[PDB]
């Protein structure tokens, strides 16, 4: 996240870090005690067995006792199209169920088909790069963003920080967009590089997949 | 440091040498980072600059991962997925410009 602020510790207890042996590579959202939701492009080319799912984290540089760590048993997709970046959503089933506490909680999703209009105020978040030429965040970052319909397409939810070079960056893929307390987006792609100040960030539109999501997690 | 095999094909033509590019394994990398590395060898080894690629009919590379997966990257696109991956999982990179 470029141009954001530190989240308060465990303010977003549904927030998930997906990690390889080399550490954090994508975000995700806890959507049931045994399921997380991310971007399909995050795991398209990785070995499912190499992924560690880290819940309850705040500072990735610390050994936090709040954390619960799971493996991935299998993934579920729904028509991911890498060429057109359509349906960029994946559900990862965990090898167990998280224990719900102050620091690890299930997110709430919108109703199927709900669309956000131009100007709705949302919050993006993640541990991605702090700037175009910087390293990944240690502390979870958040950023006030606004939904825009210009320079977007109907297949995405797009967000912008007007007048500022601020936005998601590498390592933020798969992270949630929170609007009105509900997860409306999954970070999918940027245009013109990170934090261009010219083009909005594109999120996978979660509300279009709610029926599907519910069938997997039941 | 990791040395990744790569080949360059320009207008269908490929060469018989073996070449490797130096990639950092100190942290996870992005496709923006990999684009810069690919463009670096296109410039040094073929005289194809960043602006030359804007006028090419096609400019892409394919990352082959050791698990048999692959990702095709269009070098003429300024759209990036903001994910990270390990350079150690890269088997080879096939660079193709026309
Ligand atoms: C569910 O999986 C976790 C995580 O397993 C680790 O991460 C995976 C991606 C894979 O790399 C595994 O080989 C890793 O061990 C299990 O937690 C591990 O459990 C073992 C055995 O008790 C323990 O020695 C490790 O230290 C644990 N690792 C962590 C990070 O906690 C967990 O046991 C699994 N749960 C079930 C019910 O199978
Ligand atoms: C910046 O955003 C915060 C948080 O936004 C709200 O909470 C997110 C999780 C998401 O649901 C968004 O759609 C929400 O708008 C704003 O904090 C809120 O501020 C109002 C007014 O001061 C207050 O009544 C709420 O309690 C706050 N909510 C939380 C969760 O703290 C903040 O106002 C925004 N700032 C700007 C300048 O837009």
Image (tube, grey):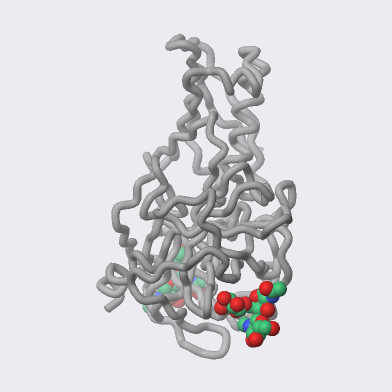
In this rendering, the answer to whether B25 lies above or below A182 is: above
Percent x, y of residue A71: 43, 68
Observer-nearest residue: B41 or A37? Answer: A37
Quadrant of image for the N terminus of chain A: bottom right
- How many marks can you see? 0
Q: Is residue B41 left or right of residue B93?
A: right
Percent x, y of residue A76: 31, 62
Evaluate whether residue A173 shows in this view.
yes
Evaluate whether residue A65 shows in this view.
no
Q: Residue at x 34, y 69 (%)?
A: A113
Task: Specify the farthest residue to the bottom.
Answer: A101
Q: Residue at x 44, y 34 (%)?
A: B72
Q: Residue at x 46, y 31 (%)?
A: B62
Observer-nearest residue: A144 or A43? Answer: A144
Q: Residue at x 34, y 51 (%)?
A: A80
Percent x, y of residue A163: 72, 55
In this rendering, the answer to whether A206 lies above or below A30 is: above
Q: Is residue B33 left or right of residue B73?
A: right
Percent x, y of residue A50: 45, 57
Quadrant of image for the C terminus of chain A: bottom left
Q: Quadrant of ligand 1?
A: bottom left
């Amino acid at each position: 996240i470029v141009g954001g602020r530190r989240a308060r510790p465990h303010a977003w207890p549904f927030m998930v870090s997906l990690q390889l042996r080399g550490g954090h590579f994508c975000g995700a959202t806890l959507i049931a005690p045994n399921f997380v939701m991310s971007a399909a492009h995050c795991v398209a080319n990785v070995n499912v067995r190499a992924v560690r799912v880290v819940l309850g984290a705040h500072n990735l540089s610390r050994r936090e006792p709040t954390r619960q760590v799971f493996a991935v048993q299998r993934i579920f997709e729904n028509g991911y199209d890498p060429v057109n970046l359509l349906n960029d959503i994946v559900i990862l089933q965990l090898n167990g169920s998280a224990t719900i506490n102050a620091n690890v909680q299930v997110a709430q999703l919108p109703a199927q088909g709900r669309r956000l209009g131009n100007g709705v105020q949302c919050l993006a978040m993640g541990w991605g790069l702090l700037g175009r030429n910087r390293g990944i965040a240690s502390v979870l970052q958040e950023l006030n963003v606004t939904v825009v319909t210009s320079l977007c397409r109907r297949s995405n939810v797009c967000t912008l920080v007007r007048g500022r070079q601020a936005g998601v960056c590498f390592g933020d893929s798969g992270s949630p967009l929170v609007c009105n307390g509900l997860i409306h987006g999954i970070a999918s792609f940027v245009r013109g590089g990170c934090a261009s100040g010219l083009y909005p960030d594109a999120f996978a539109p979660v509300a279009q997949f709610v029926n599907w999501i519910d069938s997997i997690i039941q | 440091t990791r040395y990744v095999p790569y080949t360059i094909a320009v207008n269908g033509t490929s060469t018989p040498i073996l070449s490797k590019l130096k990639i950092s394994n100190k942290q996870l990398i992005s496709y923006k980072y990999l684009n810069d590395k690919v463009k670096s060898v296109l410039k040094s080894e073929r005289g194809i600059s960043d602006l030359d690629l804007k006028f090419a009919k096609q400019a892409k590379y394919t990352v082959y991962f050791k698990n048999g997966k692959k990702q095709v990257v269009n070098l003429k696109s300024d759209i990036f997925t903001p994910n990270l991956f390990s350079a150690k999982d890269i088997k080879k990179i096939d660079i193709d410009v026309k």
